[PDB]
Each structure stands twice: as C-alpha cells, then as structure tokens.
Image (cartoon, grey):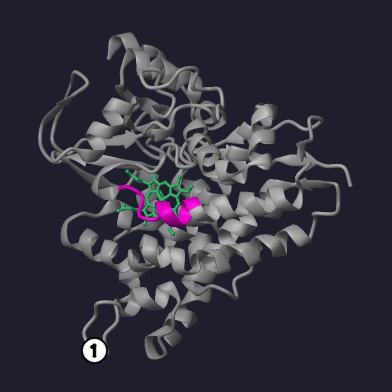
Amino acid sequence: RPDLAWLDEVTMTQLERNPYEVYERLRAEAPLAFVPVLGSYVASTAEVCREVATSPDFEAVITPAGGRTFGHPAIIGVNGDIHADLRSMVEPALQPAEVDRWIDDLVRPIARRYLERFENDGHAELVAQYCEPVSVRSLGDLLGLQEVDSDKLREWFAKLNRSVTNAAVDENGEFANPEGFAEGDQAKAEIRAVVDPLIDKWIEHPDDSAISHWLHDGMPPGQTRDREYIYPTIYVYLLGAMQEPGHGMASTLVGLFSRPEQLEEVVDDPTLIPRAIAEGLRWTSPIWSATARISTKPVTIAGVDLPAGTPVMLSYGSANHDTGKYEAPSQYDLHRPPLPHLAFGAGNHACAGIYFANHVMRIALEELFEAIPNLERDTREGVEFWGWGFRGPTSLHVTWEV
Ligand code: HEM
Ligand SMILES: COc1cccc(OC)c1O
C-alpha cells in the first residue's frame, strides 16, 4: 500500500518500547493495515477490532510466534468442537457464582503474606514484590501448583511472553530472531518436568485443583483428557492468566500516581477500586496485541478487500485509545464515564476469566492501600512500560513515611 510506505521502517523494538505513536497513525491512516515487521494485518481501532472479533466471517487463529510457542490445541487458537470442549473445560472455576464463593479466602491471605514482607520498609518495587507474586500465587494455588514457587511462575510467564511476542519477520516473511523461541522451549521443558508428575497423580487421585478438573470434568467414567490435549491451554494460563492481573494492578497504580488527587480519592474510598482498575486496563491494556482472527471467506473490512485465510492481529491496546470513543485517551482519568472497553477482547473468544481477574486485582489493591495508606511513587525512579503483545510497567518503585 503506497501511502503507508513508512510502515516499512517501523521496527519491532520501536513497537515494544512504545507502540502508541505508530498506532495513532494507523488509527487515522488505515484502521486495518499490513505491518511488515509483524508479517500480518493489524486492526487498530475499536470499530475494526470489535468487528473482526465478533464477525461470523472470522474465526480464531494464533499469532505466528504464539503458535511456534504453544502448539495445538491452544484454547486461543482453535474453533468448533475443540474450542467448545476447551471452553467447557476451563469455565467451571471461572463462573461468577463459583468465584464469589472462595475468591476472598484465596487472594486476601496471599496479599497479606506478600505485604508483610515489606510494608514496614518505607520502600518497595511493587511489580516484583507485590503485583506479580499476588497474581501468580493466587492462580497457581487455584490450578493446583501450590508447590511451584512464585519466583518460578514469574520466570515462566516472562520467558513465555518473550517467545510468544517474538513476532519480527524479515524481508522473506521468516522469523527474524529464531533463537528467541529457545527460552520458550526451555520454559515448556521445565513446566513438563514439574507438571507431568502432578497430572500423573491427579489422574489416579482427583482433587479440587483446577487442572485435576480439566482432566476429569465431563469425561466418561475412568477417563481423563489426554495431557497433550490440555498442555497448550496450560501454557496459555502460565503466560497471560499468570501475568495479566499483576500487570493490570501495576498499570492502574501508575495511572493513579499520575493523578495524585485521584489516588487520594481511591485510598479514602476503596469502593472506587473497581472503577480505577477498569480505567487502568483501558489506559494501558495488559493484553495489548496478543490475539488474532483469520477470515474464513473473502471479506471487506475498513475498505480492505481481504481474501479468505487472512490473519488479522487484534491490537486491543490501540483500540482502547480510540479517539472516536475517548477524550485524551493517553491520560489516566478515574472519572471517565464507564464506557465499554476491549481490554478483555470480544466475541466467542473473549476472555474467559474476567470476573476472577477483576476480583484478584481489586482485592490486591484493597489490601495494599489498607496496609500503606500513605503510599507514594518514588519520583527519583522512572517507570518504563514495555511490550507490544503484552504491555505493562517493568518496575514500580514506591516510598512511604514509616
Ligand atoms: C487483567 C487481567 C486479564 C486481561 C486484561 C485479559 C485479557 C484477555 C484478552 C484480551 C483475551 C483475548 C480475547 C480475544 O482475543 O478477543 C483473553 C483471553 C483469555 N483469557 Fe483473559 N485476561 C486477563 C486475565 C485472565 C485470567 C486470570 C484468566 C484465567 C484464570 C484468563 C483466561 C483467559 C482465557 C481462557 C482466554 C482465551 C479465551 C478463548 O480464546 O476462548 N484471563 N484474555
Ligand atoms: C498469546 O497468549 C495469550 C493470549 C491471550 C490470553 C492468554 O492467557 C489468558 C495468553 O497466554
């Protein structure tokens, strides 16, 4: 496309570092555009993302580097009967009535445990010391990985993140950085060594862990889902389900710190924490551009005639800055009206764990503000955000008077 020749000079590092300038141009110039370094069409506006995500003429497809990492059948990358089974497999523990039975007793003790390690220090780096540990320890316990330390769960989702978002392609459409998949492969090898004995035990001795239920639920007597059939969805969980609540927490805190009067409002009135988190997810979407759909027949979208079999990346993080929907979207504003957002996706492949994720983030922020009501950002340190596929702050240094 001639007028978009500038996209030929967009680099993967630029998008990782800050994708918002390029995507602001895309939303104005070409809401559906082929980005050469990504090797794919990308949807940048709310209208196009929503249309593709909910269209009967599209189905799910995994991004190329996502497929290289996860294989088949990743719940995010399959359709039809297999997708229906995998959705029925994961949905029981995510049902709102079920989450509300036990989410407080799960997350609140975990939050307190991590807070107790630093709440009297006067200083902390909240990403590593609080947001990521609460996120992974909560989900890890739900899954049945109680004995996998939070440090290891965090390492796994970091390696899986880098492998899944190793998206850069060269002039021939080939992956430009094939060595970048190696740490994904090594994370998977470590996960197998840890989880295979757990699956061995759950097959014979089912318990209340989610993965035991993934093996046994809805199966004939004495049968379990094959472990090779469920492992790719385990990997999906060990990346985004482990990573994203911690990133949503942290981005919400950075946004609130950027509006000090609003941080004070939320500390004074913790019933505003859910609204603060919803704005945080719009403001810096944790899953920024990590899923995709593929056309199943010829379609015209945003003036582009697409053949059947065309993948389209859903850059929801860009859609959530659509100035057709929001005023000054790069500014965090708790008092924005509660409008629809796309941080959880849309359609049949929309996020399955919204209700759980929102509660994890809410409880974690509740306990943090109760423990450290005078929390302040350490302005001597910068906050850098990183990530095009998944985006969040790489650290969050804070201080408080002890
Ligand atoms: C703030 C935290 C989270 C955010 C922002 C988020 C966002 C998303 C997004 C954008 C997608 C892709 C939707 C699409 O392609 O249209 C997704 C998929 C998914 N998420 Fe969430 N997620 C979060 C946490 C979680 C958690 C904690 C779990 C599990 C306990 C979870 C389970 C899933 C599943 C199973 C899918 C795949 C759905 C499917 O393909 O059918 N997510 N999520
Ligand atoms: C590409 O990887 C993912 C995409 C969307 C959601 C995920 O975890 C829930 C995830 O791991």
Q: Residue at x 42, y 54 (%)?
A: 355
Residue 384 visible in rendering: no
Residue wearing tag 1: 221
Which stretch did the figure color magenta?
Answer: 350-358
Vertical placement of residue 237 versus 93, above or below:
above
Quarter that holds the N terminus: top left
Vertical placement of residue 365 versus 87, above or below:
above
Residue 352 forms part of the magenta stretch: yes
Badge 1: residue crowd in 10 Å (few <14, some 14–19, many ≥20) = few
Say which of 17 and 315 sits in front. Answer: 315
Residue 96 visible in rendering: yes
Image coords of residue 174 (percent x, y): 37, 38
Identity, as a three-letter code, of the amino acid under mark 1: Pro
Q: Quadrant of residue 54?
A: top left
Circle 1 sits in a helix, a strand or a loop, which is it?
Answer: loop
Q: In the displayed structure, does residue 198 sit left or right of residue 393? A: left
